[PDB]
Structure formats: structure tokens, C-alpha cells
Amino acid sequence: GRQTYTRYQTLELEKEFHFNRYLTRRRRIEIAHALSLTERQIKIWFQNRRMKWKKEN
DNA sequence: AGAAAGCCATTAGAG
DNA sequence: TCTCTAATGGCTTTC
Ligand code: NI
Ligand code: NI
Image (cartoon, rainbow, N blue to C red; front, side):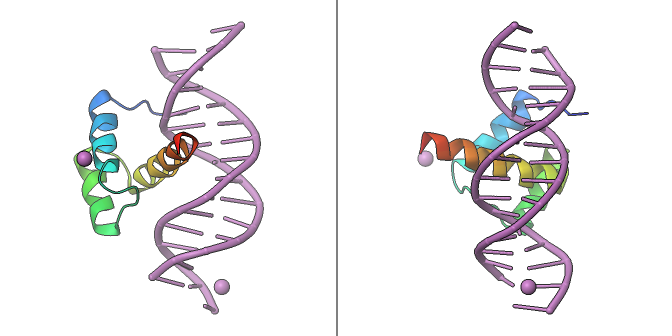
């Protein structure tokens, strides 16, 4: 099964991605707690978002 | 070194 | 039926 992300979670992440397309371990834990997601989800979201940003270039 | 993070292709589920 | 993206898996890369 797959969880669906709220607007707030997706908005707060996209806002983060605006500043740096990669995350540090300290920040990655911070974000996972604030959005009530796992460290793994945050990593994966950025993997996908970086791939999505690649197709837009 | 080898754990941890990435890249990339691919899949599958939510709505 | 169709779209988008969470999630996966098998590699390579970074530290
Ligand atoms: Ni700006
Ligand atoms: Ni090695």
C-alpha cells in the first residue's frame, strides 16, 4: 500500500526543494519529524523530485 | 572498507 | 480509463 501526501506535506517539501535539491542528515531528520513522515520517505520524495526536476531541466 | 546515499527504470495504487 | 507519484529494486557513487 501507498500513503497519499497532504497539500501541506507536499507544499512544505517543494518549498524546501526550492533552496537545495539535496538534503543533509540533520535536516532530513528535522523534516521527517515536522511532516510526520519517515526519514526514508523524505529521501525517496527527493529522489523522485530530483528526477522530475531532471525532465524539466 | 562498507554502511549510506544516490541514480535510474519500473511498477502499482490512489482518486 | 487515465494521471501522477509513492514506492521498489538493482545497480553505482559518495563518505
Ligand atoms: Ni528563491
Ligand atoms: Ni566498496
